Amino acid sequence: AAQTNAPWGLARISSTSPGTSTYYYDESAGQGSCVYVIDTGIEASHPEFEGRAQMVKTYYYSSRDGNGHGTHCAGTVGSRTYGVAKKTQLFGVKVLDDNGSGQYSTIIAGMDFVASDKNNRNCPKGVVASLSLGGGYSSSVNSAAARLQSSGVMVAVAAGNNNADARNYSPASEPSVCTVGASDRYDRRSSFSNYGSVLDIFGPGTDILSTWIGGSTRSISGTSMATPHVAGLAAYLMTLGKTTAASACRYIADTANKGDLSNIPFGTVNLLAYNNYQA
Ligand SMILES: [Ca+2]
Ligand SMILES: [Ca+2]
């Protein structure tokens, strides 16, 4: 399948070179996989989700996304127009408030919730969790991420937006999950993207068009935007049977575009997520 005039990030993950505008993908499109978006919530009623999104847990007064961040990320995972895996099932877990903030205790609870809840869902092709959040180093937060991964869920997390070594941030610094940096449309490391040896992979993160609340759309930037590209890609590859939850991050790194990015510090991987599609 081909989506013409795609958002640049989608086009980029299906090309060996920057500057293309078509997103090439297999028609299976993540059908049968499930992605948990652990964030400010999801506006499930947005036409772009086609009934494939639902809120399953909130830690606040409402399950509504009053912010937009969660809806944007969910859109990059699996919306019709803006999504990597256009037929995946999306589950929202609201661990962040409508200001985009949350306590570590709540974020940890949300991860433990997904590890259990997945056992009640029909996700025959596998389960992914996308975490576009983080803060300063916490061994408890890292441990929760490690547990979620260990339970059989592909965990993708944002590297962070401090232009610093991600070793000082959580859950970015947990080695067992998939830590995602951001790039821009000219194959440069995004100027805000964290780096360091704990990064596993880069994905598109600057000027990313996706869904927003109020049935709208907008373009924003961050490692928060790169992470759902990788989460969606994992769901897509799992549906194709190319990899499993335990090994998806490794497989994505193995099959990445290598050496395409500029402004990568020595010691940080030069790997850009790629779906290796061939018609
Ligand atoms: Ca290339
Ligand atoms: Ca890792």
Image: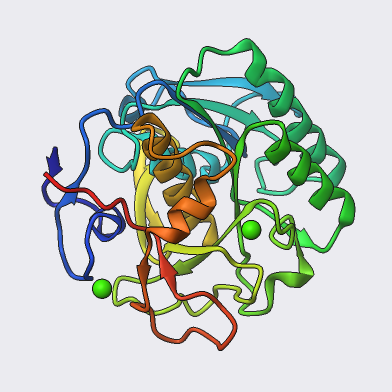
- Res. 205 visible in picture: yes
| Quadrant of the rendering where the C terminus is positioned | top left
Q: Is residue 121 above or below residue 252?
A: above
Q: Is 232 displayed left or right of 140 in the figure? A: left
The residue positioned 33% from the left and 57% from the top of the image is 274
In the drawing, does residue 40 fall left or right of residue 23?
Answer: right
The residue lying at 33 percent from left, 41 percent from top is 83
State which quadrant residue 200 falls in: bottom right
Vertical side of 18 occupied by 171: above or below: above
173 up-or-down from 63: above or below:
below
Question: Which x, y percent locates residue 153?
Answer: 62, 34
The picture quadrant for ligand 2 comes to bottom right
Expressed as whole percent of the image width and height from the top left, the position of residue 152 reads 64, 32
Residue 222 visible from this viewpoint: no
Residue at the image point whose x is 36% and y is 46% from the top: 210
Q: How many marks?
A: 0
Residue drawn at (14%, 37%) of the image: 1
Residue 49 falls in which quadrant of the image?
top left
279 relative to 62 in the view: left or right: left
Task: Name above or below for residue 43 compared with residue 273.
Answer: above
Residue in the foreground of this view, choosing between 219 and 87:
87
